[PDB]
Image 1 (spheres, each protein chain N blue to C red):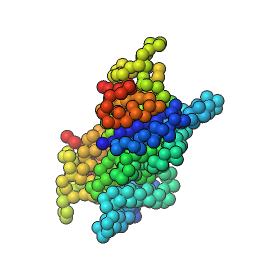
Image 2: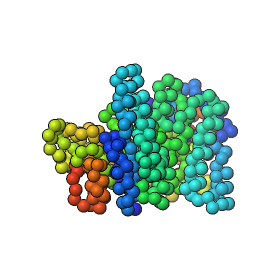
Image 3: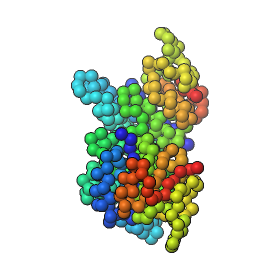
Image 4: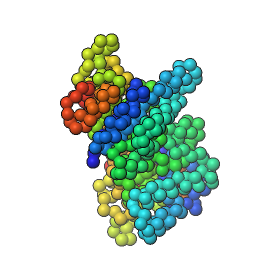
Length: 209
Length: 211
C-alpha cells in the first residue's frame, strides 16, 4: 500500500535527517514538497505587484517542484512529474518525490486561489493514487486548539476544523470525500513518522470523518 | 459559457480540414480531444510483434494522440494546450482549443492502462475534469450499429458495456454514468450534425445514457 507524506517549508533546513530516516523504512512512500524557502518570494510578488491570484498560484505550484528537486539532491531519492512514472519507480524502489506542478496544472480541478496549498496538493495526489494514508510533516506536534493558548488536539473531525484560521479549508473536503486517514506530525521527530507507518501510537493530530 | 468536449476519431484523419473549418464557425466553447489519427496501426504493430507490454503501448498510444492534436492545430490554426489550466485561458479569448492529452493522462494515471481504454475514455476523463456535461464522439459512420455488414443504427446505448459494432471503447458507458455526461456518437464527415447537437436540433446519431 502507498503512503503520501507532505514536507512543509518550515522543515526545509531540517529535511536531510527526515529524508534519511524515510529511506530506511520498508514502506511505499510518495513525498510531496511544499513551498520550501520560496513562499515569502511568491507572497512578495502578489503583495507588491499586479500579479494576481491565478498567477501567484501557477508560480507557487512550480515552487513545489523546486523544493522537490532540493529534496532529491540532498537525499538521492528519484523524482517523477507524473504518477505513471512514479508507480514504475515504486515497483523497484520504496520512495519517490513528486514534482506536483505538472499534475496540478494538468487537471486544474480544485479552485486555483490562495488557501489551496501543498497540503491540498498532497491530498489530491493521495486521491489520484487511491492512497488511504496522508501524513503532513510540519514544525510542531500537530494542530493546537482554536481558543488562545489552546492545547494539542490529538483528534479533530472534518466538521470541527471549519472556522480554523490555521487550516487549508479545501483539505477536509478531500480527506472526508476520499476516505483518507490524515496525520499532522512534527517532521523534526522522524521516529514519529516511522511509527505512523508501522501503525505504532505516537504524538500527532489525526483528522478523521 | 459552458464547455463541450468533441473527440475526433482516427477514421476522420483525412477529412479533418472540413470538420475543423466548420467547428471554428460555431459560437460555442469547444475542447477538441484527438485520437490516434493514422498512428494506431503502428502502435498495435509494435505490441503484437514484440515484447512491448500493455503499459508501454499505453504510454506510446497516449503520445500518439498529442501528435494527431498537433496535426489538427497545423491544418486549422486552432491553438493547443497540454494542461487544462492553459486550455481555460485560451477559451476566455477564443472559442476552441485542441488538448494534447498525454501530459494529463500520464500525470493522473487514474484510468486502467489497458487496450480497451482509448481517446474516447480520455475525452470523457477530460470532460469530467472540466465539469463539461456534453461529450461528442465524431466517427466515420452515423453512430453505433448492432453489427456488420448491413447492421441497424441504434438510438441509445443504455447498458454498462457496448454490445454492437463500433470503434467506441466498450466500457465508455461506465465513465459516462460515473461523470453524469451526455454522450453523442455522430458522423464527423457531416459537421452540420455537431452544430445541430450543440444547438439542441434533431439529427442523426446514437446517444449513450445509462437508463
